[PDB]
Image (cartoon, rainbow, N blue to C red; front, top):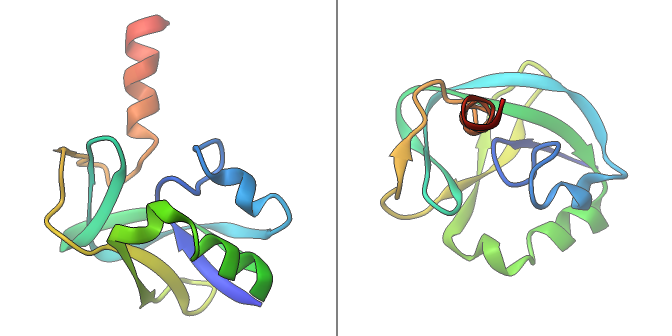
Amino acid sequence: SVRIAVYGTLRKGKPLHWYLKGAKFLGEDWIEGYQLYFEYLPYAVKGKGKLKVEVYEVDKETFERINEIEIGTGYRLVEVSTKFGKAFLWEWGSKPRGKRIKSGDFDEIRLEHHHHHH
């Protein structure tokens, strides 16, 4: 069993969340020392600010499957502290791209959707 903290693509409702359909959701938390950027993909890089994450417990097979996904190419595995204990997080390994999401919450993009269609 591996504990992971996801801030983007793997979060509930996001493009790759189906990989976590069998995982156990522990709750959300905030990781200090990270900034969030978004172009076509979400990027968490070290910097001043806090990052919203969803923390899950996944089995070995599930973790290995996720860590094999092609899109994970540009991210590297790091460890972060969460209120549920240490967890792994996929940190973007290059300069971030796209606009900064000031709230540190990937859901800010949905708020934009809300503003345009509702």
